[PDB]
Image (cartoon, rainbow over all chains, first blue to last red; front, side, top):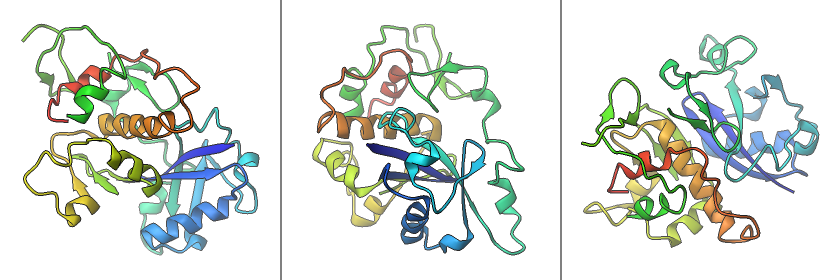
Length: 118
Length: 32
Length: 91
């Protein structure tokens, strides 16, 4: 029922607490009220795929097992801007998920996104 | 304070403590 | 609540969970003065975003756990990285 997601705009991660009945467009509206950025230029990429604004979280695979309160589903937020090539840096369709090399040769935690430092 | 108590209520780790290695971001395992 | 880590990573926390977190005795009373501005833009020093993320997730979990999720067991003591957070001492 509950959905815990994290809208990560590279250096800015926004914790979003929504429900399975909430649409992707609603998430953008939430971000709009925080970062003051138009939803039209907002691009939400989950699992390296583009979410559908007209679809609900339940249809986007935002299951409570994936979106846990102990580990929210990290969604990439790409903001479209003219001339600004920063968008490409946050686009999984071009740039791979940013991960520190020193934090790479580690194990997994208790849930998704969580890592275990050796 | 908060985390000092919450950490124990998160994971009971009886390992050794040692100054964090600047190479990464974690405490070393030795003694002091 | 906007958290800022040493890596220049900003973390926006939903006030819904923040309210509950504020009910718990946190390190907010630690420093001399925690003015309203400090409550808005919280800049942490020597604290990496990675470890801070786990703290935020634990807080979020605890907020729900001690609310309407007390039906499940305590946090899985699998990743021994909680002691690393305890190394801060003043947290």
